[PDB]
Amino acid sequence: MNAPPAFESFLLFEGEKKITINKDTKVPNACLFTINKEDHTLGNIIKSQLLKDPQVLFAGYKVPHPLEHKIIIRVQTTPDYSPQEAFTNAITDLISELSLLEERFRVAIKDKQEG
Amino acid sequence: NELIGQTVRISQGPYKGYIGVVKDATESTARVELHSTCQTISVDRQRLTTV
Amino acid sequence: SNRPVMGIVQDTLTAVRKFTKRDVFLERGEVMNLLMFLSTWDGKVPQPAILKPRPLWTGKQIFSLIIPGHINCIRTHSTHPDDEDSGPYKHISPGDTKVVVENGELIMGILCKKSLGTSAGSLVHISYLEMGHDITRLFYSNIQ
Amino acid sequence: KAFEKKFRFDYTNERALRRTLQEDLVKDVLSNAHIQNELEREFERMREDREVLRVIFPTGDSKVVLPCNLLRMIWNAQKIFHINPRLPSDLHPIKVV
Amino acid sequence: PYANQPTVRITELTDENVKFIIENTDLAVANSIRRVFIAEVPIIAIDWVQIDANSSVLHDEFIAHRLGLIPLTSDDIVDKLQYSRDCTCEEFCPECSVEFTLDVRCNEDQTRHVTSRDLISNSPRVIPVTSRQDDILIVKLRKGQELRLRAYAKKGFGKEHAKWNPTAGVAFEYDPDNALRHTVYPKPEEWPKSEYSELDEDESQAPYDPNGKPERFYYNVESCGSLRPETIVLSALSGLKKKLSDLQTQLSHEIQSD
Amino acid sequence: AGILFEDIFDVKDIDPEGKKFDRVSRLHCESESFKMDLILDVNIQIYPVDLGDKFRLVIASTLYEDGTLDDGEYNPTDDRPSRADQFEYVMYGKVYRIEGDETSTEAATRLSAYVSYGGLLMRLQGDANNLHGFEVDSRVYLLMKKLA
Amino acid sequence: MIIPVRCFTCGKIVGNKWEAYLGLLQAEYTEGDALDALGLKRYCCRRMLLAHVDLIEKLLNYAPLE
Ligand SMILES: [Zn+2]
Ligand SMILES: [Zn+2]
């Protein structure tokens, strides 16, 4: 009766914005990346790849409510670096890692299929 | 308003392929009870196909 | 009965007893994930209780961040020995069974129903009387 | 005996007052007779308060229900103003009275 | 500049599962790969049933629900197939759906088993997996009962409905010897050793490694039949990379539009 | 340069009252030089301590050789040369009470300093001339290294 | 009423294994050995066949309406 459709887990409705940056003024050099229609799948990898960055002083994600489909990532950096740049670098490193993983997986499949 | 009571098919949007009978209609919005699920949704009339 | 009607209950109570034991050590990512859920957090990561060999935070530091204002409260854990307060280790508790919240910081002690429950003089009661209903509402939510 | 040891302000052991009070206050307390009469009257008033308590609570049960938690408020004052309890105090006893 | 360099070993590659080990990656990457196996690998499944006749003992939603759970061979078709919400056709076209029909009547005096063999597709490569073993029983028909229906199978992924889950069981494991004390056994000798334990029978746990983090991850990705298990893994890596790429494009727009 | 107390302790007792936490063990130690007494909760999972082990205990008000005070905020990126580089186990805590044997008349001869390192409590009791740098609610740094 | 298509927990296909399971049971297999011969290793899929009640056989005992 009040069941949400199964596609609001992942589909942006018209006018919803995929990611918004909010520079919180509570502490210097921090941002709040509010990502819509995402879950722990991207929040956790982005958070951990941000934690590999030595110029990132804080990195954490949260789902404010599991019945809503929204990820809040909070990144704080050293002052000679910006949270937006940290987020972009984290996504590039995740993409390069997954590309390498896919290519090595194809190589391993081709090796085992032949023998 | 001839749309009310007619079996209708949603042709655009996330509900594409859902069938139902219109309950109440405006010039731009209809209340279509879905045949597939147990809901009466609101859908823009550009995304509806009568049959 | 001049006490709170509502306190920390069930899972949060069991896990705040587990969380505030003396040997609960949180790593950097775990602390940042827990600080994501602190609504009253000022954005400053506290200095870890252990810095070397690896930086580790205790559960008492994160709960000290949860504890609002500068609450001053003293309780005892449920398993506090009767002969400890008369012993030599009155203020250096071997079992972590004496709770001391000082300047809104959990100095020592394992929290339980005696400290975070609906008893009179408990931590949520002292928080209400000293800080007001809004701060204590945020305290309840942050604990949970 | 314990009531007098704990609540009656001694003003005759000056070398003990020099640990609790600063030099100006201890010179005032050892000299000014008005201060000493007022401190004695404070102790006398606590002694009739004690007898009144003995009448009100005849079973000797000290747990009462009262508005302001005075001990916690004193602790709050100690933490707010960073009161070192190893130093002599600048608080005159007559200011307390 | 801080990307991992993860290596892969396949240890078992059957037609029904792939068992592999990933070294030198983070736990969050490994878990997101395991989550995309279950939730974000798109396969083809029936999501639109018209029932022209149903004289069986099971009602129409029961039949339709069972038809959605029949796995269809999604290899090499689901990649070039469109999501029907993205396709510009009015109802259903061969660019976004595969049409299935079933027409069974039981006139024989014994019970007719309507299996997934009776599901007939118009596409010659999106068929029931069991039709390509024994077949998946949809309904049993008595004499005179019939089931005639038309079904469309669209593309979707398991985050929407579990009938688009391509996997049977995604076994996942890291640190089998508990050298990181991520789980604390009250009595470590009561616990059976893993498939991947390197300890001899005398020792119950590895010694605690204080400098260690999870680095080696063991997977066993069983496939329900729609995709080959290596196609499940490769499609998951491609889908995770695509989710990150789409997020990075949206983030680039939001950064340059500040 | 901010060093409140420095000594060499050797462990005389590990958990006299029993092992009460799995990952924290209480050491009872005595000092060879100043004849101090030490009770200390130590994370023995990351820093194991044996009975009879000898360590050099340092209690500092700051981690910098400049003596410059910190803010109590975690700064993992501070490349300033730290006193923590010469020690194997550094904790950070707040001294919460200073007991003493003073009376109403006579000053204190034995002082006890109680410090809480995030809940891992330390009591350092000895001569009052050795615990002058300890005043309540001051953040101190415990630093120790095992000697050979 | 009828055998589920998928295991509820994991999603392994068990809807093609019911008649094979009954054929193995008629062939004097123990139930655990029949479940082992069908390839049901996880105990979540084994309780799908082990605990199934084939009620559709009872509902086919009634003559159809048409
Ligand atoms: Zn189409
Ligand atoms: Zn199963």
Image (cartoon, coloured by chain):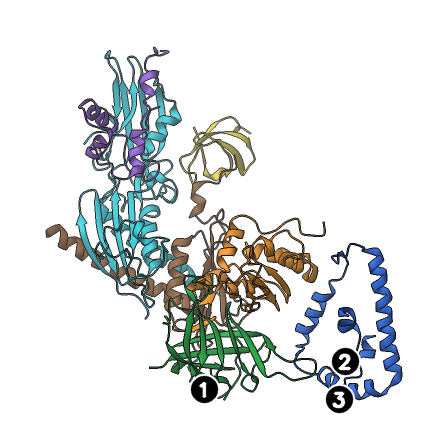
Chain colours: A brown, B yellow, C orange, D blue, E cyan, F green, G purple
Q: Secondary structure at mark 2?
A: loop
Mark 2 vs mark 3: give the one in front: 3
Residue C56 image-quadrant placement:
bottom left
Camera-near label (3 vs 1) is 1
Quarter occupied by residue D55: bottom right
Q: Which mark is residue D91?
A: 2
Say how many tags the image has: 3
- Which of label 1 and label 2 is nearer to you? 1
Mark-to-mark CA distance, 2 and 3 = 11 Å
Give the amino acid at mark 2: Leu
Task: Kindly report the distance in space between the C-alpha atoms of the residues bearing marks 1 and 2.
Answer: 41 Å
Which quadrant does ligand 1 occupy? Answer: top left
Q: Quadrant of the N terminus of chain E?
A: bottom left
Q: Quadrant of residue E45?
A: top left
- Looking at the picture, tell me which residue is in the foreground, E102 or E112: E112
What whole-number distance in Å separates the C-alpha atoms at marks 3 and 1?
37 Å
Secondary structure type for disc 1: loop
Q: What residue is pinned by disc 3? A: D23
Instruction: State whether residue C53 appears in this view.
Output: yes
Label 3 SS: helix
**Observer-nearest residue: A73 or D43?**
D43
- Check the residue under mark 3 and report the chain it is in: D
Judge left or right: residue D67 versus residue C75: right
Which residue sits furthest front? D1
Instruction: Tell if the residue under mark 1 belongs to the same chain as the one under mark 2.
Output: no
Is G32 rendered above or below residue E177?
above
Q: Which mark is residue F33?
A: 1
- Note whether D3 is above or below E99 in the view shown: below
Mark 3 on the same chain as mark 1: no
Three-letter code, disc 1? Ser
Which sits in the foreground, E19 or D89? D89
